[PDB]
Image (cartoon, coloured by chain):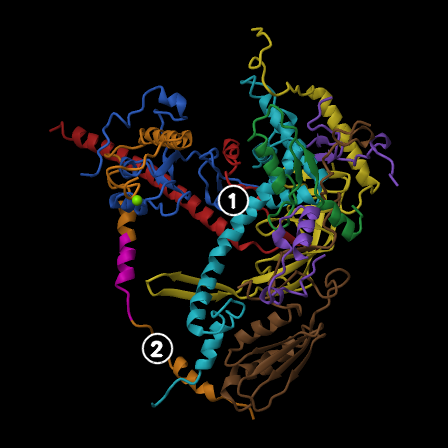
Chain colours: A brown, B orange, C red, D green, E blue, F yellow, G cyan, H purple
Amino acid sequence: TARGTPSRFLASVLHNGLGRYVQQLQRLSFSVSRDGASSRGAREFVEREVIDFARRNPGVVIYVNSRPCCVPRVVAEYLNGAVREESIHCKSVEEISTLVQKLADQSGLDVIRIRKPFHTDNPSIQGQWHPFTNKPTTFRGLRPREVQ
Amino acid sequence: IPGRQWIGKHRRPRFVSLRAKQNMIRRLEIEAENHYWLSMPYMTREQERGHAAVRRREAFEAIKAAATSKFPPHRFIADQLDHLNVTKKWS
Amino acid sequence: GGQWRLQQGLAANPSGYGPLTELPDWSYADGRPAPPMKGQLRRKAERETFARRVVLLSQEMDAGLQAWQLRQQKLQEEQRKQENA
Amino acid sequence: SSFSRAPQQWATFARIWYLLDGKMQPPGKLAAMASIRLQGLHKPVYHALSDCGDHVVIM
Amino acid sequence: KFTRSRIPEKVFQASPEDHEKYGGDPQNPHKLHIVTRIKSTRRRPYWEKDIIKMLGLEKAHTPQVHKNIPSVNAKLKVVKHLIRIKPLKLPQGLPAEENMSNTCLKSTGELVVQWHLKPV
Amino acid sequence: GYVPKTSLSSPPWPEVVLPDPVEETRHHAEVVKKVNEMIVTGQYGRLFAVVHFASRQWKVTSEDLILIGNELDLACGERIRLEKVLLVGADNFTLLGKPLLGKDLVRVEATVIEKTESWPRIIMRFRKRKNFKKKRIVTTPQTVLRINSIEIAPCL
Amino acid sequence: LRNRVTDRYFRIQEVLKHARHFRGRKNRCYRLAVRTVIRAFVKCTKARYLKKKNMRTLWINRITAASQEHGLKYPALIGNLVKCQVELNRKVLADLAIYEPKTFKSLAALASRRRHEGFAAALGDGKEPEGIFSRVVQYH
Amino acid sequence: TYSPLPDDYNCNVELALTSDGRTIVCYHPSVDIPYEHTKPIPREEGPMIEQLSKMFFTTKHRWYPHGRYHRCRKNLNPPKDR
Ligand SMILES: [Mg+2]
């Protein structure tokens, strides 16, 4: 629940869409057991789609480590230093190509609650409301019951 | 109020506002328009006799052919040999 | 404020029909139009089956009328060929 | 517009002293005017936590 | 005891004052109603709950075209307090299949058969 | 029909009289020529636009983030024309549609920066004394739209 | 005992981690903490209905505040912006009250001019030409 | 001469339609405050809390301290926006 969890505001990393779009994914690190039943779907991702994924995003360098693991992992590292290690244990090929394209779409910010759905840094153009908007001025600025 | 306000012999009095009246007078006007649109049938009972009997019979014969066509599904060598794949490895 | 909308023949909910929720929300900046919304495809599906069911009922009203006037004209001639011999 | 971020915040949440002469006025038409201002319900920057009530002076 | 209600026949005969108040014509009546549920079938008897599913009226404010034949009408009299009946007018003709997709039932009761989303 | 001036003889509101509609359509086109010529020379500063995107109205300026709560089926970095803009204000003028503005008047642009999922949102039901307790963790897919440019054109 | 439960520390800690910020003994002892975590999780989903409601009455209260600086009332503004076919919702109208108040002085002017065009139209009931801001843009 | 609002305080609202009727145009230039509407520049725990309620027009209850449980619950790195 939102009082038990932290929060943050809506933000991009380095104004990600203004000048150019920079893909925020930096690395992907797969660990797939060759003789191992849990990595049987992830072995086919390395077989089929890890060449095809590595040509849709050239700015992400991919590692396939292939050691004796019991639970295969993908360690997605982002440009701002956040590390998402998600577990692809006993997933199909289809559930990983959605898993890995989701890590290549998101920014490296926390998946804690976002406070507002909008973030303007210059939110007012006609001047923010202060109490003296929509009030009339009087002659010589006299406050009430001011004689001179 | 002596016991359980809205039940019993000595109930709590409830009164009608204009709001609850204009909610009720406006339901009555919607109602009375339906008395007028139900007042003029296009055919009579003699003209619509059997006028949808060819489609009504055909609709049930698709409900009947839906119900008499239950069976266990076909069972393949595909789903059985595909469990041998759980020990697929690399060389 | 929505009963003034019904007097003009607009929908009482402005998220009903009309240019606010039936126009496409976005287009590409290459100019090419978007693939359709999932709510507009569903709204066009319930509107084809309502126009499918208008025609089906409006044909069966005028197929049972023209079947009835044949049966009275069949049954006049069944009398007109029976006031004889 | 174009203030620095601290004096503009002092502009929006400053509190205003209202005079409200209540001679021959009913004390609940006086009350329903001051109670809007003491809550700050006449500011579009109203929020219950924001503490946006103003000073009312009823003579 | 609370039973079903017979609505007598001095109710569904329309006096000539009524054809001015509503837009109907006795000579050449309409072919189709648009029935729309507007009031819940909860706290209503089970025979009124059955007729509401029979007519295709499970969702409120969902319009439904029906024939103006005297048998469909007899089902409409039992649940006339839960519905709003209004005649399906067609300003253009009934939509042939070339115009079957770009139709739109307006709220006035009528079914326009070309529905662009451009002003006039 | 003359009533002497008592308290209830008059209404409490002042009898506001609306102007002559041939003086007023002439004064209207006198206004629109000013607001057209404030656009032709570029007298505006930055513009806010009020856009009916996904299901709701965002009030939107250049260079700001907009969090959508549904997946938009776009590659990240793809540029979008947001149609359906219904108010375009500047410092000195506004143009509001009826309901929407012309497509050849204002062009709002937006870029897909990121496509996240929401934080895990708990759905938990409980009824006392009934052994009824169900718990469900849902996340929604979300995109974030960076609005790049609100442009305007002299078509009034 | 053939097989007993070894994973029970990790089942306690799924419920105790959600209760860590509570008061008293409902953060430590699991039997009290499970009844408060449940009640906290029930309140969290029933507050998705009251976040939406409490935002709208806050928008309505901020619009009532700003349309009274310009003399109108809330119903005279909101109902009359509909008759000008201006389909701005309450969230945007509260944003124009605070962040762009020259436009809220324009929308309170549009709503009031349409309001005067409705008094001046419905006095001479019958055929009279509509006001400038009373024409509907019909769509077909 | 008709004014939909008394254009005296905020801006001079000019309303107009286009010749289509499909956009409502407003021109609202900002209002300068006149020079004549302006003035020139003029050039124990107990008694302490009573003297702070008088200064800021609060009650006494926001000046008493809070215990430790509320002090170390407070976020010290709050999410800054804008
Ligand atoms: Mg009692």
Q: Which residue is mark 2?
A: B75
In the image, residue B70 lies in the stretch drawn in magenta: yes
Q: Are marks 1 and 2 on the same chain?
A: no
Horizontally, residue A80 falls left or right of residue A67, namely right
Which segment did they paint magenta? B60-71
Q: Is residue D46 left or right of residue C12?
A: right
> Mark 1 — residue?
E102
The quadrant of the image that shows the C terminus of chain B is bottom right
Disc 1 marks which amino acid? Asn
Position above or below: C9 against E41: above
Q: Position of residue E113 (x, y in %)?
A: 49, 39
Is residue G80 shown left or right of residue B52? right
**Location of residue D26 by image quarter:** top right
> Ligand 1 shows up in which quadrant of the image?
top left
Helix, strand or loop status at disc 2: loop
Rendering coords of residue G13 (x, y %): 49, 76
CB-based contact (under 8 Å), mark 1 and mark 2: no
Q: Residues within 10 Å of mark 2 (few under 14, many from 20)?
A: few
